[PDB]
Amino acid sequence: EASGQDLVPAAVEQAVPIQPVAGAALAAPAAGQINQIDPWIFQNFVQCPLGEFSISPRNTPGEILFDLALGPGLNPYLAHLSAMYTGWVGNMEVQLVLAGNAFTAGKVVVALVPPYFPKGSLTTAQITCFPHVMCDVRTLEPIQLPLLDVRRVLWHATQDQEESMRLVCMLYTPLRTNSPGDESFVVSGRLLSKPAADFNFVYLTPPIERT
Amino acid sequence: EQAVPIQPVAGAALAAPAAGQINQIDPWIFQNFVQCPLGEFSISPRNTPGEILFDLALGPGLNPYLAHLSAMYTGWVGNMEVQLVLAGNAFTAGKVVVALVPPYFPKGSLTTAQITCFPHVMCDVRTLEPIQLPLLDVRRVLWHATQDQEESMRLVCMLYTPLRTNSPGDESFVVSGRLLSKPAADFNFVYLTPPIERT
Amino acid sequence: EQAVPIQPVAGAALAAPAAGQINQIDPWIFQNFVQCPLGEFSISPRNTPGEILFDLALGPGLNPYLAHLSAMYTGWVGNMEVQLVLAGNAFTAGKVVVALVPPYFPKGSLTTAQITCFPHVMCDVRTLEPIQLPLLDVRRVLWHATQDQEESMRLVCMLYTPLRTNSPGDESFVVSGRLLSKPAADFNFVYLTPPIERT
Amino acid sequence: EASGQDLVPAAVEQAVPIQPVAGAALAAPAAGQINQIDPWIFQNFVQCPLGEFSISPRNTPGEILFDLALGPGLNPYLAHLSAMYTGWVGNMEVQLVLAGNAFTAGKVVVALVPPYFPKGSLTTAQITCFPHVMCDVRTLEPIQLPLLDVRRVLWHATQDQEESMRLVCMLYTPLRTNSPGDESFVVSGRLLSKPAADFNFVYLTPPIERT
Amino acid sequence: EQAVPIQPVAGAALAAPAAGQINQIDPWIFQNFVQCPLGEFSISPRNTPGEILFDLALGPGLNPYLAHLSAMYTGWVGNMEVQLVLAGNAFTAGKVVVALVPPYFPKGSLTTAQITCFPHVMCDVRTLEPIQLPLLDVRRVLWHATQDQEESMRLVCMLYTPLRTNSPGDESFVVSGRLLSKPAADFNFVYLTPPIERT
């Protein structure tokens, strides 16, 4: 309602307890070609294809706000390029935009659930067991956070049936508002992404039409 | 906030060898932001995201003084500098994205996702200071001719994240925005020409 | 804010001479605050002060990884480190006191006055940062045995000063709090032991 | 309603115009024993026995919010110890907690009325005549302030019929709120205390049951 | 006797760049040989040579402590170290061969001749000291995932040369053997993970 700093600009990146992860440097000597994507793609963030979501005051703590897996399907550019190659390596950088109204309150948690972890429940009791961050729905700045390619093999086939370290944001505390009149501000959260330092594809293929 | 993934666009240093003259502007014009003819909008709490708040292309028509001077020359070339102002108190919430579409782009609808793929900036409705950003003259020709509007770089302003405010019984508290512009450092006209009456 | 009238409690340096081994923990476990099993509450504007928001004793059961490791050892000893998070905007008012009761105390009701007599901290509901504080292992024995829950130091969280906020027609705007914990620098297990099936 | 600094964190201790006052150092050569209380009691503040009060928007300027006299009856620890001795000396330190909602407004005044002053009226016209402080009901930090033992004799008998420099907080301006909806936040104020540098008792006695 | 035609297999130094973490083990676990779940047999004078005395693959299931820890992580990688003990006096005769089959091998019968073609050791039944030998983690992937048993290197123990002893009227004097194991120097788990209940 105003430009004040009665919000929590918690752009602080709490040190996520995880080592760096090597990207395309591990798959280079195993790809028959030399491939490289447009450097300008590494420059600006861009909304993930499924990058929109919303938190309502009737959402229950534990509901999965989103759960998206690492892969080329997180950038429109990368998704478009993935139709030309067969395989991809590397990490990703994701910004979360949660700039709800100052009359709101509530907290969510974002976790880097590793591969091979059984999908499904991921209850609120165990969401904090993973390397995670606690975010307030009133944060001004976009929250940056990495998406590393914790993998068992050299690269993942561009047909992404593989297991990748998915990133899951879950509602931790109920969303409540504080304004005196007949309205609870549902907060609209967005998700931007861009490839990490050495994200890369491997082997050129005919750019299939119906990807 | 003036950090967009763009290269510096040369203007009036690329059109000099093929222009008869390179005419200058009253330097006072470089020191006053003037309201662009259609750079204004007003967001309402019921405005759905994805709407186009404003859309306007680079050219001497964005500035009344520049439009008046254009009637006296043959061609023009160079960049401009714009700034957006938003009227919102600290009790608001919502985002607006402003992108720089290239001067060759299939017109039509743009979803709230595509708008981020251009070199752009995202702006909260609680920003006090005017948001300044450049309007570069991307082109294939050397210098644009004044007497025919050809394709130029455009600013597009899309409602990114909807407005979240309270409002009294009246009148729903729109957040109004305006856009001002002025010539950049190297905006010049080309060839002095008798001003034809119907320009 | 981590200044409570308490002395540093020695752990795993006092139990070493009488322990067969002193087993260590995966250091990664020391670097992640995990949600305690019952460290959660939600204050309402009609919650009267003096209520117990949460109450929980020190032990390997406060951490899922520590609980899992406890099935592999005979005894444990050491301190832990906890932090409280509160979800409240700047338009709230009310205080919550968190005290460190010693590991021998007649259970029962505690008035809003007695709760301040323990080493404690008072916290407004408008605190952004997590409130960190230690959980020391005050004891009479050297190292606690894993297979029997004996008396340990407890954290008690009492609603000190009631909540003062507005609220829309729904749903009265509770202020929710959560409690996370992790092992301190000198939390160790004692004697490696085959994990019996029903632990 | 938010974590902003739209409040008055006036933890400033306006210089109360009063000299320091010697405590137990004056009664030591007149007590037959050597007595001393637990040092840990001097460490943390604790809510006074009668340390709770509340300000309502219907309270009138001039109403005595509280009026409490210096003595061992201001700490649960000191009150419990007072049953063992016969007499006490020394000063006290008192924190006042007035952290009302940001939509409130109003001011109170705290004064150190000396001994032998006639109890009763203490009208709003004269509350400022004493060494006093003006406090806003929206203060974040606890307001610290001393309670010196301005006395005529060496010590006061632990039966506190004596005259001690009582401390009196009175509502100075009416409490009004500013939020738009059908509610005036009554503010709950608290009072914590702890003994000063050389507060002390004198002579041990049988710890009477019904104190 | 720990000289088999094998190369040193790198573990946890090859899986580090692609693992989020590299978790360590209670060092005490490195200092106790524990009985493998099926590492036991008993040769009789009528046992024909060529029989499989035991056969067991590398993995965290060979050690109760390692099996318990596996429920807490995502992946594992590294080598192990095993030792065989035989109970035979000086009045016996007969040989037993222990081979290291690679982690990709058509299962089926193995004659007493093929068993020698692997990197192996031959052992008389009159050996007092435990026979120590490594179990390396030959693989194609970087680090094995804890929640799915994939192919790993196996130890196979075949009765090479039959037993030649006298025996009283009872009970024919079997020669019993047991197999113990423990983690090698660079056996690690990969990614700390909440222990799912049915692991």
Image (cartoon, coloured by chain):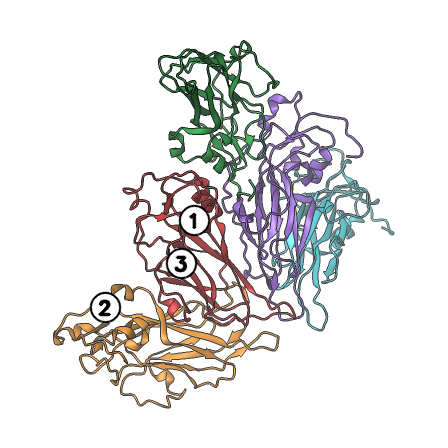
Chain colours: A purple, B cyan, C red, D orange, E green
Label 3 sits on a secondary structure element that is: strand
**Residue ID at (33%, 45%):** C12
Instruction: State which quarter of the image contains the C terminus of chain D.
Output: bottom left
Q: Position of residue B172 (x, y in %)?
A: 71, 68
Tag 1–tag 2 contact (CB < 8 Å): no
Pointer 3: what residue? C154
Q: Nearest to the eye among marks 3 and 2: give it.
A: 3
Image: A153 above or below C86 = above
Quarter of the picture holding the N terminus of chain D: bottom right
Residue that numbered label 1 is attached to: C60
Tag 3 and tag 2 share a subunit = no
- Estimate the spatial distance between the alpha carbons at disc 3 and disc 1, rounded to whole Å: 13 Å
Give the quarter of the image for residue A150: top right
Q: How many neighbours does mark 3 have within 10 angstroms: few (below 14), some (14-19), or many (20 or more)?
A: many
Relative placement, left or right, of C30 versus A112 is left
Name the foreground residue: B198 vs B85. B85
Task: Characterize the local packing of mark 2: few (<14), some (14-19) or many (20 or more) Cα atoms within 10 angstroms.
Answer: some
Picture disc at residue A77: none
Residue type at mark 2? Answer: Ile
Identified by mark 3, the residue type is Arg
| Parent chain of label 3 | C
Residue E177 vs residue A22, the one in the foreground: E177
Q: Position of residue E26 (x, y in %)?
A: 41, 36
Specify whether disc 3 shares its chain with disc 1: yes
Q: Chain of mark 1?
A: C
User: How far is disc 1 from disc 2 in space, using C-alphas?
Assistant: 37 Å
Disc 2: which chain?
Answer: D
